[PDB]
Image (spheres, coloured by chain):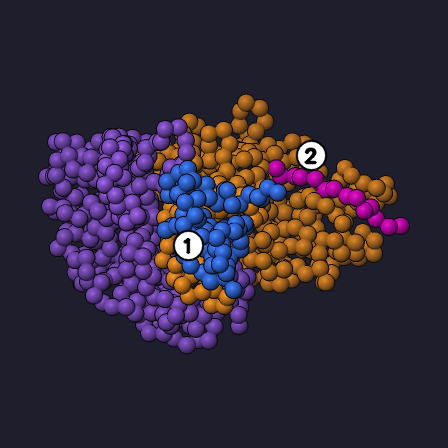
Chain colours: A purple, B orange, C blue
Amino acid sequence: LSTASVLAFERKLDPSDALMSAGAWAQRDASQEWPAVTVREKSVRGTISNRLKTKDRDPAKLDASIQSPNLQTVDVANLPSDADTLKVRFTLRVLGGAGTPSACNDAAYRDKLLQTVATYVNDQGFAELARRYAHNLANARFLWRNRVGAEAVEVRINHIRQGEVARAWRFDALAIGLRDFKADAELDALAELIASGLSGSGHVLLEVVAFARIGDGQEVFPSQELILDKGDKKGQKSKTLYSVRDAAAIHSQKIGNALRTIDTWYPDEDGLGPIAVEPYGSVTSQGKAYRQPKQKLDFYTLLDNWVLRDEAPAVEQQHYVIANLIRGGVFGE
Amino acid sequence: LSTASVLAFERKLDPSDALMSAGAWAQRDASQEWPAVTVREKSVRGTISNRLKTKDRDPAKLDASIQSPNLQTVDVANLPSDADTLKVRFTLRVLGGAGTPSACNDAAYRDKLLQTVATYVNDQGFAELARRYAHNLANARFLWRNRVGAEAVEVRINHIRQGEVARAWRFDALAIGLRDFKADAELDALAELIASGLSGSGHVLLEVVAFARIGDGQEVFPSQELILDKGDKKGQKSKTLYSVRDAAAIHSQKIGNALRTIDTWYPDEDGLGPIAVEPYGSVTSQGKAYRQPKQKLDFYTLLDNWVLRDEAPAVEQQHYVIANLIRGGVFGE
Amino acid sequence: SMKFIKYLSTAHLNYMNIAVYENGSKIKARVENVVNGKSVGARDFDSTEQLESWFYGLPGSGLGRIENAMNEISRRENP
């Protein structure tokens, strides 16, 4: 058997864009009406700070650079001066059916993949993966830099059965760790809800709301946009923040990245911690791709061994391959 | 006597471009005014997770390629954050008399085809094809990726005579199944109305209104505008969505392809579900060449057998041929 | 014999970047798709110092500057 020339997987655990708004702590119970954080605009005069080439380490060149203007315009997002917390809400659909590809050529590779994922599910459920996704919902990984240096963070998760809420949860994102994975009653209830959602045995719709007590007027961090500073008139603003109508927003894929930070068996070490699930699993923000294909832990290697040749890897790498299938992607040649 | 070489069967059951709007569930009854979903803009920083070679590629080149991000720009479309229902509205002209073409060489072949289509109108008017078109209208095949993950899908179908209504059905696309085709009294009524509408008995004009609870802020999927990109003009942009005057729309081609899933007796398989009805009938996404021309079960060779040799296979193959001529297209090279 | 040196940017743009090859005593700049290696236009150079004086002489800052670079190389050089 040869693997197909076209593979595809739709994503499960698909979130929406976050919506940031600010208000007061101990008023977060009545928070359906808080005004949204807006993206304003300020001016910055920079400086000479990058490394010199050491061929330009002259007195006169540095003095001309210091007399030279470095005026820029950037976007900033702050709280109002009387608000000290940040409300962030988004919804999350849990689809299920996480073994069936949405596009395939080979009808034999398709059926082999189906009973391979099926004997994974029969061997053990989605319980460990849903435990780790319930952890990344429990703490506030989707608050990326907003969590860093916060007084107290709190996460509210509701289950939406109809127009009315069915099941609720109330967490503490600082006491619940960021480094390991633990057990608790409400964590295991949320993990079993996610595990029932991933096995096609129900419809799960979760809205998640996070509150981060930072301080009055501090700088919140919406996600930043890609702009090409080319040669237009006089230079434009050099930092664009993502927004929607009258509200500063985090992208959906940034929250989706912060949910799938699961992997703890990339072959480097346990000193760093969990990284995001990824084929050729690469933390690009530190420029190093862990799980290189020069070892035998790459996702394509594990897939082509465990589906074609029917040799099973360790249980931890089985969790890695099923989390890759839940992620979605463009697989095949 | 040979047959005509230049033939052009024409379009029939023409749907309009489906427009999308957004509002709240259970207030969908008095909804003719919902604001249109519009295509927004955002930026993407991703890794490179596609398959990579081990021949004729340097190790340093792939280490530099995986560890460096990819900064593309894509289009999206979401619901508003207080609106959880995707409304899809489109109209459907049902013309009548799709038997004869209007591009013929041979006059003897043309009125011979008139003889056999008057034979089919004589013995039994359009019944099982009308069943299958009314049942594809009954579920939400026109909702392609909008269907899966929704907890409640409704189809409302009105009929047009003047500035007034003639009949108001109501179809539950979750209760009505996806695969096994059945019949019910409202489905009998709609299939009878468009059964009259197919055999040239007059004029039938429908408009179909759909609703779907997905959740506030979630991703909708309008169709994608194509671009060639063969070599040069690579581009900063990817994923160009399709639009109309300030709205997010679905193409007529793909909602028509959603209407034309009829054939359950294709010779490759019969339990995987129906495929698209076309000459050399094979779905594009799978890529497997279903309905190989080297059997007698095409539209080409089967029509050449059925109009000259005057023989016939079982009645279902003739239902496929009549669905081919209601579809339209080109017969001959 | 074209030994790879470096990519010209930190980030890829649309799976597209500029690879730098050492072609003898000259030096090559190819506009390559990073996942399959399909080149859509190259330009000869000799020294890395003049190549950087050409690249930093382009209008723009960062990915806009390498957009200018790929638009400059990706057109046919006139006779």
Q: Nearer the viewer, residue A149 or A92?
A: A149
Q: Is residue B230 shown above or below A242?
A: below
Q: Which residue is mark 1?
A: C7
Is A279 colored magenta in this rendering?
no
Q: Is residue A288 shown above or below B38?
A: below
Q: Amino acid at mark 1?
A: Tyr
Q: Nearer the viewer, residue C10 or A322?
A: C10
Q: Are marks 1 and 2 on the same chain?
A: no
Q: Which residue is mark 2?
A: B201
Residue at the spot x=20%, y=35% of the render? A78
Q: Which one is in front in this view, the residue at disc 1 or the one at disc 2?
A: 1
Q: Amino acid at mark 2?
A: Ser
Percent position of residue A146, x then y = 20, 45
Q: CA distance from mark 1 to mark 2?
A: 68 Å
Report the chain holding disc 1: C
Report the chain holding disc 2: B
Percent position of residue B293, x then y = 71, 59
Percent position of residue A204, x then y = 32, 51
Instruction: Confirm or deny contact between disc 1 and disc 2 (CB under 8 A).
Output: no
Q: Tell me where the magenta segment starts and ends, as one range.
A: B1-14
User: Would residue B240 be found to the left or right of residue C10 on screen?
Assistant: right
Q: Nearer the viewer, residue A132 or B191?
A: A132
User: Would residue A311 be found to the left or right of residue A315 on screen?
Assistant: right
Q: Residue furthest top?
A: B163
Crowding at dot 2, Cα within 10 Å, few <14 / some 14-19 / many 20+, comes out as few
Is the magenta region chiefly helix, strand or loop?
loop
Residue A20 visible in the displayed image: no
Residue B233 visible in the displayed image: yes
Residue at the spot x=53%, y=45% of the render? C74
Q: Quadrant of residue B125?
A: top right
Find numbered disc 2 in the image and state the secondary structure of the residue it sits on: loop
